[PDB]
Image (tube, rainbow, N blue to C red):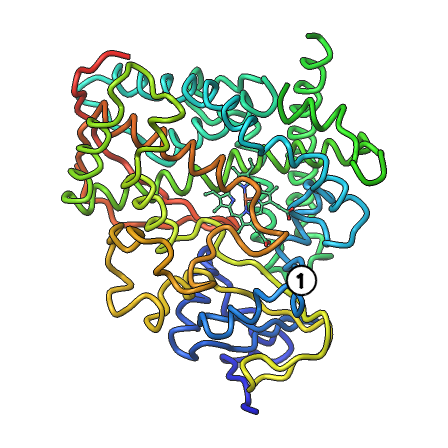
Amino acid sequence: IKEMPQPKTFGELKNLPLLNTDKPVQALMKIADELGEIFKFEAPGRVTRYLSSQRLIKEACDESRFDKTLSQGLKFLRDFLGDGLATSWTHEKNWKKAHNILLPSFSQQAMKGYHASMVDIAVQLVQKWERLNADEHIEVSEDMTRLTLDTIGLCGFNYRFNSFYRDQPHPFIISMVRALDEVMNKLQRANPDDPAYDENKRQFQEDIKVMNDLVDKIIADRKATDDLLTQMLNGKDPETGEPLDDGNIRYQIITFLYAGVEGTSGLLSFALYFLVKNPHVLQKVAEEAARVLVDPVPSYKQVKQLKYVGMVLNEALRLWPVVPVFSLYAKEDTVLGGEYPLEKGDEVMVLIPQLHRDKTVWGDDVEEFRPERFENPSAIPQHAFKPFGNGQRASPGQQFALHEATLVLGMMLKHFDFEDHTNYELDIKELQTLKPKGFVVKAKSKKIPL
Ligand code: HEM
């Protein structure tokens, strides 16, 4: 039975000032590197424990001992995501119902139905890059976000955001990013009732209205005229026979569009970054892309044969898991690793970037980008790789995300050579999800028609 380490406290503010940064997850990684596999973190009125080792995280991932909790971050996201799937307690009224109703929208049959829409948007991206002049460059994170929002819009809702017909981000992206930024600010605010924050609160309500205005256009357009929206509006819970309430449906739509703005866009941006920084890996992916993608547009079967592209995407998720933390609570009194006693309700945070750098399960070379790590998935120890979370509360979008990401990276490397023309230094923007900031490249067309 050991005493848990804790970083510097600041009187009544406890540890809160340590995360007074634009990069709090990166700050928590530095604390983990100082204090080791577990440390206590206190803020006014709340305590959590950050886990960094596979040894402790494997116990946290035991669903008989631990269930999902909402971090302060996820609690604030309920301001516009409500009790959608991601921001619901496991035993809250709409979690199990929504989970059951939306399950067949991620079926193998659903995935085959989505492929044609993913190709539509991927073709738009390739055509944009083909039409750039010699003196121009690509804003990588920006164009990856255009693609992922358009893909979930078309695949999920038969709605065209038409992000490639806009120089600035779609108003929905502008408002969602501004809302996510306000939540990052709220996590650092000790005195939220201060009148100095009245303008912030007004702007927050305005951004929530813009997002709700778009949800109205998606529903109106469906009324005017078989996908995720069909299942939301018409699907009934097989257990109870009850459909989703109109209010919950709206929260689910914004939740799935949030997957469109953050997550897959981060992965694709991180993936291209690692490729331009590791030219031998880029050459290998370019060779696979050329060999497998023999048709003008990729088939479902051809995307499944892009094996090394899959390994590249997994190695991007290892180093920079784009959803970097998930939170759990002790269902009963328990002892973590035979050293740390927890009371019922005690909260733990899985620091995924630190888990993915645990030398005891990954070896010495944890900082090296080596997709060859994932040549044999079965050789990776249990609970050593958790970019999609854990158990019944794990990502339902894993297959969707990796299919989209494989298709896009495959086509990109089939159609273009890439130059890191500015010698870009990785700068990671944090919104409770991770994405490169200011990442720019030049593309050279291989002149292969679509
Ligand atoms: C690289 C891409 C993605 C990553 C890394 C990712 C990661 C995650 C993680 C870690 C969680 C668990 C969060 C927690 O325990 O608090 C999660 C939940 C979820 N993800 Fe994903 N995700 C990705 C793509 C997607 C996509 C494309 C969709 C939808 C189309 C999606 C929908 C969801 C939903 C609805 C949940 C909540 C599930 C529930 O609790 O019932 N994700 N995701």
- Give the percent coordinates (x, y) of residue 415: 23, 22
Q: Which residue is drawn at the image coordinates 65% and 24% (left, top)?
A: 214
Q: Nearer the viewer, residue 269 or 59?
A: 59
Q: Looking at this rendering, what residue extends furthest in the bottom direction?
A: 1
- Give the percent coordinates (x, y) of residue 11: 61, 80
- Give the percent coordinates (x, y) of residue 290: 20, 26
Residue 283 occupies which quadrant of the picture?
top left
- Give the percent coordinates (x, y) of residue 192: 69, 57
For the residue carrying disc 1, how many other residues have a C-alpha within 10 Å: few (<14), some (14-19), or many (20+)? Answer: many
Q: Is mark 1 within 8 Å of ligand 1?
A: no
Position of 216 with respect to 357 (left or right) is right
Residue 60 occupies which quadrant of the picture?
bottom right
Q: Which residue is drawn at the image coordinates 71% and 45% (left, top)?
A: 79
Position of 54 with respect to 68 (left or right) is left
Q: Which residue is drawn at the image coordinates 64% and 18% (left, top)?
A: 226
Quarter of the image with the N terminus in it:
bottom right
Amino acid type indicated by mark 1: Asp
Position of 189 with respect to 344 (left or right) is left
397 relative to 108, above or below:
below
Q: Which residue is drawn at the image coordinates 69% and 44% (left, top)?
A: 201
Quarter of the image with the C terminus in it:
top left
Residue behind mark 1 = 67
Position of 154 with respect to 204 (left or right) is left
> Where ligand 1 lies, by quadrant?
top right
Determine the secondary structure under disc 1.
strand
212 relative to 66, above or below:
above
Q: Nearer the viewer, residue 327 or 429?
A: 327
Q: Nearer the viewer, residue 420 or 236?
A: 236
